[PDB]
Image 1 (cartoon, each protein chain N blue to C red):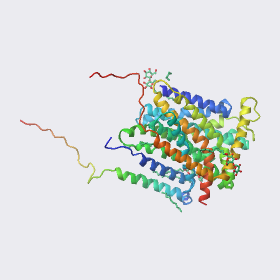
Image 2 (cartoon, chains in turn cyan, blue, red; image 1 turned 30 degrees about the vertical axis):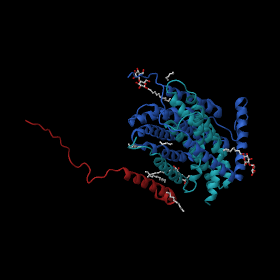
Image 3 (spheres, chains in turn orange, purple, red; image 1 turned 45 degrees about the vertical axis):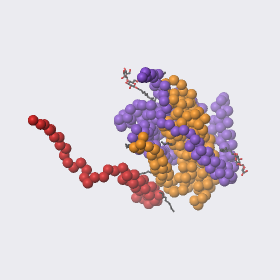
Image 4 (cartoon, rainbow over the protein chains, first blue to last red; image 1 turned 180 degrees about the horizontal axis):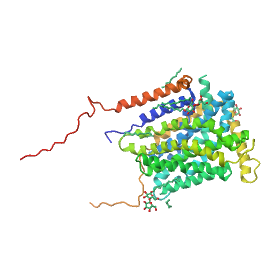
Length: 169
Length: 240
Length: 49
Ligand SMILES: CCCCCCCCCCCCO[C@@H]1O[C@H](CO)[C@@H](O[C@H]2O[C@H](CO)[C@@H](O)[C@H](O)[C@H]2O)[C@H](O)[C@H]1O
Ligand SMILES: CCCCCCCCCCCCO[C@@H]1O[C@H](CO)[C@@H](O[C@H]2O[C@H](CO)[C@@H](O)[C@H](O)[C@H]2O)[C@H](O)[C@H]1O
Ligand SMILES: CCCCCCCCCCCCO[C@@H]1O[C@H](CO)[C@@H](O[C@H]2O[C@H](CO)[C@@H](O)[C@H](O)[C@H]2O)[C@H](O)[C@H]1O
Ligand SMILES: CCCCCCCCCCCC
Ligand SMILES: CCCCCCCCCCCC
Ligand SMILES: CCCCCCCCCC
Ligand SMILES: CCCCCC
Ligand SMILES: CCCCCC
């Protein structure tokens, strides 16, 4: 207890920095990464709501389930931003037109994944019997996080990209 | 064994949600085959690194499924979209589709590794717990990309049914006929909605700050624990 | 590879920054000594009559 305790902000600060750097290399831009990194909270709110309204705690299973939720939501945002930038760079489309083409093309695969995984973790949410405490804890945070991440991201990612692209020329 | 059962159940539920969108048996198997191939592969990587089959590594497999199907779905869906927009045969659309996303798939895995790797550097007691998830999930993602570059393309070129240019399955009769027309209309409603959001913009930046402050409040209110107390079908009573 | 990073100087910086990060973090946790283990090990049996 007394020798060492709570090194959480340190490792997730590095994580946040390295994710930014990796995105900066991917997009060849110091600014465009922010359009993807601003989706993190969209999946966190839903996980926190789910865990709060089921009387669960911020534990290991909530944390790893939240990193998974952030992973997919960020991955969805990356492919939306990538498709938009492609249309602007290669096809030479406008900011708005390209962003609308991106989200239009990326809707089906986003929902396909979201529904598959949300429904896939249903057995864990409603789980009873041996180890249900861990199953309930995993599924609850993920299901809650995935639904907010899915519904919010599809409307917010296009705002993030358009807003970020405009502030930085 | 209860977590192993929810893996099987999750793969079956993945299959059904895939059949709702792809609407043909062969196409539905491409994402459904990719998951167990990667997951089984992940067990061999845990074996190489001296890790064990445990609650945390097993839940690593369950959480991984989301990242695995997405890799497979991104590849399969994009081929279907190319086939529908241009009318290329499966083999040509596959070559084309892989050409424009294979770079991103590899890039995404390195961005996502930067999310999961860090918590493998927690120290002492808590360290080993978080390290089980990190290595399980990161190993699965690595295999997922390698499976997305070898098998998924090969299956897409051989198992996917040729789609004619402009055909979004709206001409089908039955449930798929109605669903395809519902989704195509819903996609127009979506883009029309986003198109309107992009004109406002400012009122969503302020709404986003509300979601972030809402998040912050819930985070500090929510009590923090470590690992739940499980009913293990046994307990003890002390007489002093 | 040189031609690739000539057109992508941000990628070039990212690789360099990540390497400096791993190093900066490493320094904090590295042991300090005059030498490593340079001495061959010894075992002593002690008895009394
Ligand atoms: C499709 C995705 C993959 C799903 C996940 C894969 C399943 C994971 C199972 C985890 C638990 C496995 O636990 C492992 O079970 C196998 C049998 O199956 C046992 O192996 C057994 O082999 C034979 C099987 O008849 C027995 O006669 C023998 O007694 C025993 O050695 C191992 O001793 C045990 O350690
Ligand atoms: C300690 C080790 C230090 C090394 C750390 C390295 C981490 C950085 C990884 C970031 C991931 C980058 O991911 C990589 O992005 C570049 C962006 O030019 C993509 O590259 C692609 O981008 C566009 C495509 O329109 C073209 O300019 C380029 O020709 C093409 O290859 C790759 O397809 C992708 O794999
Ligand atoms: C507490 C968090 C709440 C999360 C909410 C997340 C978003 C919810 C789903 C998106 C629904 C928004 O609905 C969408 O709003 C925009 C802007 O108001 C509307 O846009 C409409 O009004 C604006 C201005 O009044 C016009 O410039 C535009 O031409 C017109 O279409 C869209 O017609 C509507 O479809
Ligand atoms: C793939 C990433 C490998 C992670 C390396 C684990 C480091 C564990 C040492 C932490 C100190 C006990
Ligand atoms: C012609 C294309 C060459 C692309 C070279 C990228 C390799 C980067 C490796 C970085 C290792 C640290
Ligand atoms: C650690 C990230 C450093 C960001 C570089 C800033 C770019 C400015 C270019 C004008
Ligand atoms: C271990 C400190 C709390 C974790 C918050 C995500
Ligand atoms: C209770 C169903 C059997 C568990 C092993 C998969």
